[PDB]
Amino acid sequence: PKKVLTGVVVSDKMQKTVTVLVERQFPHPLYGKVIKRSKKYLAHDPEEKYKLGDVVEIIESRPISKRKRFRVLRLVESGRMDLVEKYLIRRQNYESLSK
Amino acid sequence: MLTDPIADMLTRIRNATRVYKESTDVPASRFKEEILRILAREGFIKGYERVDVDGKPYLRVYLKYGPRRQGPDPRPEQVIHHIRRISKPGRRVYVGVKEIPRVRRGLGIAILSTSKGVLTDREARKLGVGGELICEVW
Amino acid sequence: PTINQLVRKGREKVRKKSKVPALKGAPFRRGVCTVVRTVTPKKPNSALRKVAKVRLTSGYEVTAYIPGEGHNLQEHSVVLIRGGRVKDLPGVRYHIVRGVYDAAGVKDRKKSRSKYGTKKPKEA
Amino acid sequence: GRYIGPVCRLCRREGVKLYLKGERCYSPKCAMERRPYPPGQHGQKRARRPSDYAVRLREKQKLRRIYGISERQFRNLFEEASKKKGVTGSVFLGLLESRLDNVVYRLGFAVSRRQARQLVRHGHITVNGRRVDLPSYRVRPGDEIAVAEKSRNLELIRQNLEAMKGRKVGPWLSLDVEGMKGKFLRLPDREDLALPVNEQLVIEFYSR
Amino acid sequence: MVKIRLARFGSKHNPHYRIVVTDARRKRDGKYIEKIGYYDPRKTTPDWLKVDVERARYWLSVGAQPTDTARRLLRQAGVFRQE
Amino acid sequence: RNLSALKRHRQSLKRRLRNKAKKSAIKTLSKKAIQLAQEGKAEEALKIMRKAESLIDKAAKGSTLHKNAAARRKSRLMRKVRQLLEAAGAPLIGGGLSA
RNA sequence: GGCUAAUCCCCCAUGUGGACCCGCCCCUUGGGGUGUGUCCAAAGGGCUUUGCCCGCUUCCGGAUGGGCCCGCGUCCCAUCAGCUAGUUGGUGGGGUAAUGGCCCACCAAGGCGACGACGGGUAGCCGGUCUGAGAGGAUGGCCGGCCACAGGGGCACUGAGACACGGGCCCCACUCCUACGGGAGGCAGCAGUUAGGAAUCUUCCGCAAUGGGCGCAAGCCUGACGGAGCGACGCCGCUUGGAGGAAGAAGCCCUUCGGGGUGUAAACUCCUGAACCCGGGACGAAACCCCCGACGAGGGGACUGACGGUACCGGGGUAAUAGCGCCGGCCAACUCCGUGCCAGCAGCCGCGGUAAUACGGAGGGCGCGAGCGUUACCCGGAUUCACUGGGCGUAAAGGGCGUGUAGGCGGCCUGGGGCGUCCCAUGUGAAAGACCACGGCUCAACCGUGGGGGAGCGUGGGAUACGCUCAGGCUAGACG
Ligand SMILES: [K+]
Ligand SMILES: [K+]
Ligand SMILES: [K+]
Ligand SMILES: [K+]
Ligand SMILES: [K+]
Ligand SMILES: [K+]
Ligand SMILES: [K+]
Ligand SMILES: [K+]
Ligand SMILES: [K+]
Ligand SMILES: [K+]
Ligand SMILES: [Mg+2]
Ligand SMILES: [Mg+2]
Ligand SMILES: [Mg+2]
Ligand SMILES: [Mg+2]
Ligand SMILES: [Mg+2]
Ligand SMILES: [Mg+2]
Ligand SMILES: [Mg+2]
Ligand SMILES: [Mg+2]
Ligand SMILES: [Mg+2]
Ligand SMILES: [Mg+2]
Ligand SMILES: [Mg+2]
Ligand SMILES: [Mg+2]
Ligand SMILES: [Mg+2]
Ligand SMILES: [Mg+2]
Ligand SMILES: [Mg+2]
Ligand SMILES: [Mg+2]
Ligand SMILES: [Mg+2]
Ligand SMILES: [Mg+2]
Ligand SMILES: [Mg+2]
Ligand SMILES: [Mg+2]
Ligand SMILES: [Mg+2]
Ligand SMILES: [Mg+2]
Ligand SMILES: [Mg+2]
Ligand SMILES: [Mg+2]
Ligand SMILES: [Mg+2]
Ligand SMILES: [Mg+2]
Ligand SMILES: [Mg+2]
Ligand SMILES: [Mg+2]
Ligand SMILES: [Mg+2]
Ligand SMILES: [Mg+2]
Ligand SMILES: [Mg+2]
Ligand SMILES: [Mg+2]
Ligand SMILES: [Mg+2]
Ligand SMILES: [Mg+2]
Ligand SMILES: [Mg+2]
Ligand SMILES: [Mg+2]
Ligand SMILES: [Mg+2]
Ligand SMILES: [Mg+2]
Ligand SMILES: [Mg+2]
Ligand SMILES: [Mg+2]
Ligand SMILES: [Mg+2]
Ligand SMILES: [Mg+2]
Ligand SMILES: [Mg+2]
Ligand SMILES: [Mg+2]
Ligand SMILES: [Mg+2]
Ligand SMILES: [Mg+2]
Ligand SMILES: [Mg+2]
Ligand SMILES: [Mg+2]
Ligand SMILES: [Mg+2]
Ligand SMILES: [Mg+2]
Ligand SMILES: [Mg+2]
Ligand SMILES: [Mg+2]
Ligand SMILES: [Mg+2]
Ligand SMILES: [Mg+2]
Ligand SMILES: [Mg+2]
Ligand SMILES: [Mg+2]
Ligand SMILES: [Mg+2]
Ligand SMILES: [Mg+2]
Ligand SMILES: [Mg+2]
Ligand SMILES: [Mg+2]
Ligand SMILES: [Mg+2]
Ligand SMILES: [Mg+2]
Ligand SMILES: [Mg+2]
Ligand SMILES: [Mg+2]
Ligand SMILES: [Mg+2]
Ligand SMILES: [Mg+2]
Ligand SMILES: [Mg+2]
Ligand SMILES: [Mg+2]
Ligand SMILES: [Mg+2]
Ligand SMILES: [Mg+2]
Ligand SMILES: [Mg+2]
Ligand SMILES: [Mg+2]
Ligand SMILES: [Mg+2]
Ligand SMILES: [Mg+2]
Ligand SMILES: [Mg+2]
Ligand SMILES: [Mg+2]
Ligand SMILES: [Mg+2]
Ligand SMILES: [Mg+2]
Ligand SMILES: [Mg+2]
Ligand SMILES: [Mg+2]
Ligand SMILES: [Mg+2]
Ligand SMILES: [Mg+2]
Ligand SMILES: [Mg+2]
Ligand SMILES: [Mg+2]
Ligand SMILES: [Zn+2]
């Protein structure tokens, strides 16, 4: 079974490509707390069909390019910019801690 | 607000029994009531009943104690010697059926929340399901 | 610490510093003496302890103790050293192994011979 | 090693009369019938209250010197017994009693366990017909411990088995004196052994 | 090719062989595909040779090649018997 | 002081010269055909593409241009020729290309 | 420069079939089918010789082996906080068995990072192994799996497969030959030499067994392997005697000078018989092969042992190595003399300056025993990095205070989803090891056979109490 994840499109600034952020909950291996991790996957959008905020399913695919190994299966739900804003604020905080 | 309502109820019961109160009022909730059902069924309390304070619904837990003891400290033996919350917010505890603890080698209970309702260690073990390890009582 | 703190920071494993930096973790090390001096002990004791500043094949030059009643260790004596410190001598963390390459065993030793490099005497 | 040397000095040091020479530990010559104090210059001096480690070590040494088994084999047998299911002490005793030399002693073929060890090592004992010369050999229930047909003419065997006429054997052993053989019927229970040892003391000694 | 041969598993002067299906390019004591029998050359026990006949027939059907010794041991177990 | 496995080396050299030749032909012919397809000379283009495909398969007979890789070269050649003639038209000789 | 053969190379033909362009159908990424067009096949040899055997060619499938891709897991330093130009993506190409920014043209400006990028340091990884009640900590030697490397660096050729340890090329360092022009070489294969080091082996035997390569076979090769050798390095088995033997020799040590101790210990008496000396003397070895049959099934026959005259069996047969540490407390074992803060001991506390159970020797004792000690290292105890399982008023520890970002956590009621959670079924979890049972070397170590396991992850189905999410509602928190 080819892995099928579900995430949020947070970057449509590339050509025929979208950055889908995928979260996952799991108990900590030693401390048992259900912790939440995440990972960004570069998925293939050959029709520019999906835009920012779209929650979409992603499927393991034949490699399209270096770092691009997934295709957008279908659209789970339309643009919800709240998770996108959360990710953008997380990124924007990085400029405040340099020196 | 309360961060853990269930632990709040358990601590209310602990603090009440430690001074030999008659009953204690806990803010009412279906989950708390389902736990109190197991409590009263197992004999740790005389029972519970829904009540109303000035505007809001509560649960009166009627506590249980042993006979008055002799010698110094005639205070009776506690029926609930120990009651501790396990699956707290921030560290939730889930166990399979083969991972349910035998409390006090039998003399205690462990309250679980399973997909088939709120059960005890022996009840869940007989049912064959596991879940969230709410609290241990003995 | 809270569970969330342990997920963020985690417990810190404690590492133990080696009391015997004879490099490569060796149990013994060969060296050549530099000086064979006499050191006075610390607070409660008083004696003349026999110490030798051994220059090791490990690259170090450290002082090591010369056990036994008598010794024969000149300046250019080649001796082997082992762990084990002398408490009443600050800085002396190593012992000379008696019976190795220049250091004869303590003569007339009869009780604990293997610890001072003295072979079994002849017929009884 | 086998500790080989004086033995009745252990009869003295352990405080309990041991039987390491066979006879002469029954005769008024054991040096325990006449000198019950431990050996050495300081044997007759007033004893101090022994530590708990002292008590457990003395009891374990008593039980170990009774059989003449070295520390290596002793600790190995004990760990083997602790691995098994059941009471560690009784199983350990059943293991020690299952040794071929000890069985030869118990069957009256030899007067002492060390004499039995020499009888085994010199191939004078057979197990189920086949010759066996290992004291550490473990006898199973049902094994027939016999005397070699070529050794049944020896003077010592004649003496020992001529004295065994009329003597009873352990409840877990059978003896045929005419055929000069016997059978290990079962493992001995704790109630079958009259050893002056507290097994729990040895268990606690190795528990450290 | 895939072969059916013996592997040595006993100790020194105590040889015990596993009749085994493995790639010829692998070492004789290395990772085999399946153990299809065992062989004791010194005949220490009354059962000193056992072979799974159906499995040997399968591996021969798919294209395995046994050694001369392996083929002898199989023939003794009636792998090729068609009576 | 060495063993006669040097013989193998010798053989490789021969085979090397055998391979480099065939490929050097194929490549050459391919280019030639493509030229005629760019200039519209369809008859000669297909007539040379036939010979190119033949040399490709003949090289595939041995260890020179084995595997498919030969089919890959044939595919790319036929595709490029048919595409370049479509910019002009009139597939005159009707050679390798299907109707 | 010249001659020549082939299972060497080439051309044409035959098109079972396959390859490719295009079209159609099914299927859904480049899978399968179909039509026209085009393109592609081959090698002979041996006999028991016109019939078989070893082969050859094209195609489909199996089997085995592998390539590539993806989820999750994989040490320390944040006294490394910003990294990135083939960088991220696209289009079109080149390349490969195959995807890919692998490579290259052109276009777009992206990609990664406190959920720790980048940098630095360290390190093959795992099955396992050691320890631990467990959780965990430590480790990855032998054996098995995967990786990487072959003096350092780079590169292609040949091939089903290599960027090739005992193949090739170039640069560098090194060694050797040298007619000074130029060449040869690569133990991290077995053994051995040397250097370093506290320290690690024979320049041994054998193709008999197992396995591998070539060959129809005979057979050839195999420092793979099977054995032997050396080293108490480890584990296991065994010996240095057994029984009798004085109110108790001598010597030696204490002493109230009565005696006490070494101690049944010895000498001795009787008995067995480690070593050795003879004789017998293996299993491992029945296949390939040959004959019959049918070169099949089946039957029969013959050859072959390095270990090795070893194991083992029988007879004969001598009382025949014991050492090392400790004895103030922790910690089992005490006296005498010598020494006089000297000489020395010591893991920690500590002992020695006149009468030391602590130094040194003696007698005696305790502990282990072909070992005993020491040093080094790991886990343990250590609940002393505390998930299980700790703390912060005065013992080490609440930030000087606030505002607040991310993050963590979230009152009551109903419903949808089923992400966490839970259940069932199933796949996976190589072997070895670990556990249990039986069995083979006289036991054991060692080994064989069988049994049982197991988290995690994949898939199918199910549960909805709790946590999650979405939709709605409430007012006890909060705000007004
Ligand atoms: K845990
Ligand atoms: K930035
Ligand atoms: K056709
Ligand atoms: K090579
Ligand atoms: K045959
Ligand atoms: K004999
Ligand atoms: K005899
Ligand atoms: K002096
Ligand atoms: K002393
Ligand atoms: K402060
Ligand atoms: Mg998401
Ligand atoms: Mg876009
Ligand atoms: Mg692309
Ligand atoms: Mg689970
Ligand atoms: Mg000198
Ligand atoms: Mg037990
Ligand atoms: Mg046990
Ligand atoms: Mg392989
Ligand atoms: Mg059979
Ligand atoms: Mg068949
Ligand atoms: Mg060659
Ligand atoms: Mg050749
Ligand atoms: Mg050209
Ligand atoms: Mg090629
Ligand atoms: Mg010529
Ligand atoms: Mg056709
Ligand atoms: Mg043709
Ligand atoms: Mg050819
Ligand atoms: Mg021809
Ligand atoms: Mg003919
Ligand atoms: Mg790149
Ligand atoms: Mg491309
Ligand atoms: Mg392409
Ligand atoms: Mg290639
Ligand atoms: Mg990057
Ligand atoms: Mg992350
Ligand atoms: Mg490294
Ligand atoms: Mg354990
Ligand atoms: Mg563990
Ligand atoms: Mg590791
Ligand atoms: Mg390795
Ligand atoms: Mg390995
Ligand atoms: Mg080298
Ligand atoms: Mg090189
Ligand atoms: Mg190189
Ligand atoms: Mg080839
Ligand atoms: Mg390589
Ligand atoms: Mg190379
Ligand atoms: Mg080489
Ligand atoms: Mg060369
Ligand atoms: Mg040297
Ligand atoms: Mg060797
Ligand atoms: Mg040879
Ligand atoms: Mg061979
Ligand atoms: Mg062979
Ligand atoms: Mg070998
Ligand atoms: Mg031993
Ligand atoms: Mg005696
Ligand atoms: Mg005699
Ligand atoms: Mg035979
Ligand atoms: Mg042969
Ligand atoms: Mg014939
Ligand atoms: Mg036959
Ligand atoms: Mg021979
Ligand atoms: Mg004999
Ligand atoms: Mg003491
Ligand atoms: Mg000392
Ligand atoms: Mg130490
Ligand atoms: Mg004096
Ligand atoms: Mg004195
Ligand atoms: Mg003293
Ligand atoms: Mg002494
Ligand atoms: Mg040791
Ligand atoms: Mg430690
Ligand atoms: Mg710990
Ligand atoms: Mg603990
Ligand atoms: Mg610490
Ligand atoms: Mg804690
Ligand atoms: Mg603390
Ligand atoms: Mg403050
Ligand atoms: Mg938040
Ligand atoms: Mg917030
Ligand atoms: Mg809630
Ligand atoms: Mg939330
Ligand atoms: Mg619901
Ligand atoms: Mg679910
Ligand atoms: Mg296993
Ligand atoms: Mg374990
Ligand atoms: Mg057995
Ligand atoms: Mg299971
Ligand atoms: Mg499911
Ligand atoms: Mg439901
Ligand atoms: Mg709401
Ligand atoms: Mg107000
Ligand atoms: Zn006695």
Image (cartoon, grey):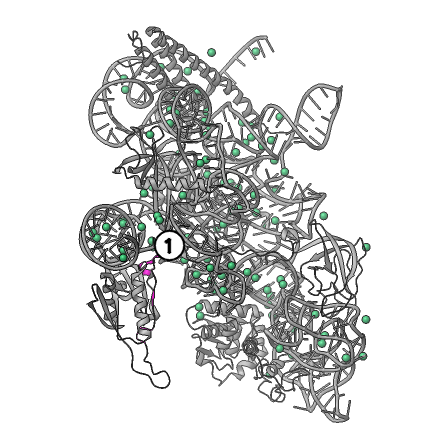
Q: In this rendering, does residue A1 appear at all?
A: no
What range of the chain is rendered magenta? Answer: B77-98
Vertical placement of residue G217 versus C50, above or below: above
Q: Is the CB of mark 1 within 8 Å of ligand 1? A: no
In-front residue for pair G310/E11: E11
Name the subunit of mark 1: A
Identify the residue at horizontal 48%, vertical 17% (top origin). Answer: F20
Quadrant containing ligand 49 reads top right
Query: Residue A16 occupies which quadrant of the picture?
Result: top left
The image shows residue G365 at horizontal and vertical percentages of 65, 78
**Can you say which quadrant of the picture contains the C terminus of chain F?**
top left
Quadrant of residue D25 within the rendered picture: bottom right
D69 or D182, which lies in front? D69
Q: Compare residues A55 and F10 and report the one nearer the observer.
A: A55
Whole-percent x, y for residue G18 in the image = 32, 23
Using a 10 Å C-alpha cutoff, classify the residue at mark 1 as few (fewer than 14 neighbours), some (14 to 19) or many (20 or more): many
What amino acid is at disc 1? Lys
- Is residue B82 placed above or below E20 in the rendered structure? below
Q: In this view, does G82 lie to the left or right of F51?
A: right
- In this view of the protein, which residue sits in the foreground, B98 or B87? B87
- Asked if the stretch drawn in magenta spans residue E61, the answer is no
- Examine the residues drawn in magenta and state their main secondary structure: loop
Quadrant of the frame with the N terminus of chain F: top right
Residue G126 drawn at (x, y percent): 46, 48
Tell me the residue at 36%/57% (across/down). Answer: B91
The residue wearing badge 1 is: A33
